[PDB]
């Protein structure tokens, strides 16, 4: 199931109901929606090591 | 200068620290060149080579 060449993230029924407020945020966006990879790329740097160091305080 | 910070992973193989200090020095100059560097031993990313940016060994 974890082979990404054969399966992709699905929105379960649960997640489809939560999209009502989560929208096409990172959690409830399909992998193929433009807003997924864009937000992934824009926000991954907020969890870099330097960012983490800067959240410590 | 941020936004890099391209991802620069630096891995070392060291017993007496020469290679480890060289590695950390590199990661220090990367930070100055806007990267998002990460330093770790070699046999800890065994199989987990970065499929993006670059990896100094």
Image (cartoon, coloured by chain):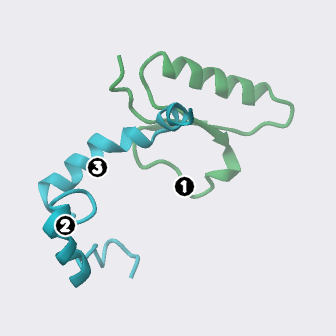
Same subunit, tags 1 and 3: no
Query: For this view, does B9 lie left or right of residue B23?
Result: left
Percent x, y of residue B55: 52, 38
Q: Are marks 1 and 2 in contact (CB under 8 Å)?
A: no
Q: Is residue B16 above or below residue B29?
A: below
User: Disc 1 or disc 2, which is closer to the eye?
Assistant: 2
Chain for numbered disc 3: A
Percent x, y of residue A55: 50, 36
For label 1, the SS is loop
Q: Quadrant of the N terminus of chain A?
A: bottom left
Alpha-carbon distance for marks 3 and 2?
12 Å
Closer to us: A15 or A10: A15
Alpha-carbon distance for marks 1 and 3?
20 Å
Same subunit, tags 3 and 2: yes
Which residue is label 1 attached to? Answer: B48
Q: Residue at x 61, y 52 (%)?
A: B45
Chain letter for green, please: B
Query: For this view, does A11 lie left or right of residue B19?
Result: left
Query: How many badges with numbers are in the image?
Result: 3
Which residue is label 3 attached to? Answer: A40
Query: For this view, does B48 lie left or right of residue A32?
Result: right
Same subunit, tags 1 and 2: no
Chain for numbered disc 1: B
Residue A30, disc: 2
Instruction: Mark 3 or mark 2: name the one nearer the start of the chain.
Output: 2
Q: Quadrant of the C terminus of chain A?
A: top right
Residue A21 figure quarter: bottom left
Chain letter for cyan, please: A
């Amino acid at each position: 199931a974890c082979d990404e060449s054969r399966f992709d993230k699905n929105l379960s029924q649960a997640l489809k109901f939560v999209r009502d407020f989560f929208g096409d945020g990172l959690f409830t966006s399909w992998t193929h929606e433009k807003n997924w990879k864009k937000a992934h790329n824009i926000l991954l740097p907020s969890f870099s090591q330097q960012a983490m160091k800067g959240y410590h305080a | 200068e941020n936004a890099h910070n391209t991802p620069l992973l630096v891995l070392y193989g060291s017993n007496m620290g020469t290679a480890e200090g060289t590695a950390r020095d590199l990661a220090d100059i990367a930070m100055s060149k806007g990267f998002a560097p990460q330093v770790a031993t070699l046999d800890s990313h065994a199989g987990n080579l970065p499929r993006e940016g670059a990896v100094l060994i």
